[PDB]
Image 1 (cartoon, rainbow, N blue to C red):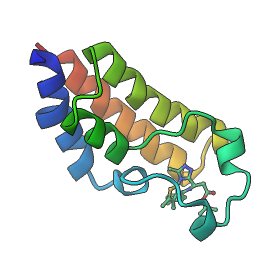
Image 2 (image 1 turned 135 degrees about the vertical axis):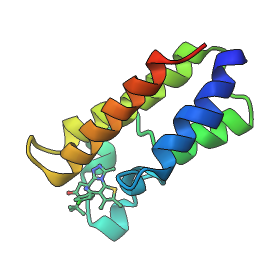
Image 3 (image 1 turned 180 degrees about the vertical axis):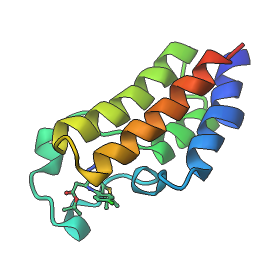
Length: 106
Ligand SMILES: Cc1sc2c(c1C)C(c1ccc(Cl)cc1)=N[C@@H](CC(=O)OC(C)(C)C)c1[nH]nc(C)[n+]1-2
């Protein structure tokens, strides 16, 4: 709960306010984006609002488990999309920021 609080107040907050965060703020809306294959290819969907709601309602038992959700979020993007896709560049940049902030965790 020392570190979970970091991930809430610092990591999540900074990722959320970064301008690349917007595709990752809600779950993928497959109807609106017309991706009928998405939730078949991506079996463990994850997004920043889920991670937040999960912190807010104390779903996590350990910092490690919150970190793995962030990583699933990014790996989901890489699996569904292609190298050189705009969405993949955004995700890689958010991932860099993410590591940057992990380095400075308590
Ligand atoms: C709201 C969301 S959620 C999202 C995207 C959007 C737009 C984007 C996207 C975001 C930003 C830019 Cl510049 C380009 C695409 N892409 C899709 C995959 C796709 O192909 O969607 C289109 C068919 C392109 C809509 C995708 N995969 N994983 C995620 C989280 N997203």
